[PDB]
């Protein structure tokens, strides 16, 4: 509350460390469904169904231009990519399995870097 604060956690490296995680997600062999925005002209149903499209290149641009206020808003966009994927793709598909794999990969790096 006013003039009463928990000890200051050092967040000075968070930007660099989120960048590193994102590089590791970008270079994963199962990243291909997520590297670029889904083409809303060429994929019937995507525009109407997926209210907030997100992809790795959009996260990279946001990160590089100071549009994440803190490390949690970064994680929310990464998770959005996988939530969207699960919304639109059957589990038993190459893309469906890719999303599950990448979400696991992300959540481990997140825990090991920050928790």
Image: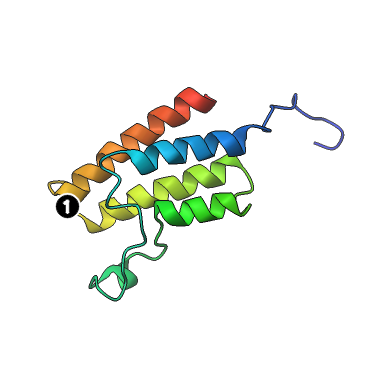
The answer to whether residue 73 is left or right of residue 44 is right
Q: Residue furthest left?
A: 92
Q: Residue at x 24, y 70 (%)?
A: 43
Residue 70's spot in the image, x, y percent?
62, 43
On the rendered image, what quadrant is the N terminus found in?
top right
Q: Residue at x 38, y 43 (%)?
A: 26
User: What residue sits right under mark 1 in the picture?
Assistant: 90
Q: Quadrant of residue 55?
A: bottom left
The answer to whether 46 is drawn above or below residue 84 in the figure is below
The answer to whether residue 90 is left or right of residue 21 is left
Residue 112's spot in the image, x, y percent?
46, 23
Q: Quadrant of residue 53?
A: bottom left
The answer to whether residue 8 is left or right of residue 86 is right
Q: Residue at x 32, y 63 (%)?
A: 38
Q: Quick one: label 1, few (<14), some, or many (20+) residues within 10 Å?
A: few
Q: How many marks?
A: 1
Q: Residue at x 69, y 27 (%)?
A: 9
Q: Residue furthest bottom?
A: 41
The answer to whether 51 is drawn above or below residue 66 in the figure is below
Q: Secondary structure at mark 1?
A: loop
Residue 90's spot in the image, x, y percent?
17, 52
Residue 16's spot in the image, x, y percent?
58, 36
Q: Quadrant of residue 25?
A: top left
């Amino acid at each position: 509350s006013m003039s009463v604060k928990k000890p200051k956690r050092d967040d000075s490296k968070d930007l660099a460390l989120c960048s590193m995680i994102l590089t590791e997600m970008e270079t994963h062999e199962d990243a291909w469904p997520f590297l670029l925005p889904v083409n809303l002209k060429l994929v019937p149903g995507y525009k109407k169904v997926i209210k907030k499209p997100m992809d790795f290149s959009t996260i990279r641009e946001k990160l590089s231009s100071g549009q994440y206020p803190n490390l949690e808003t970064f994680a929310l966009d990464v998770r959005l990519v996988f939530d969207n994927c699960e919304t639109f793709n059957e589990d038993d598909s190459d893309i469906g399995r890719a999303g599950h794999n990448m979400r696991k990969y992300f959540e481990k790096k997140w825990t090991d870097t920050f928790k």
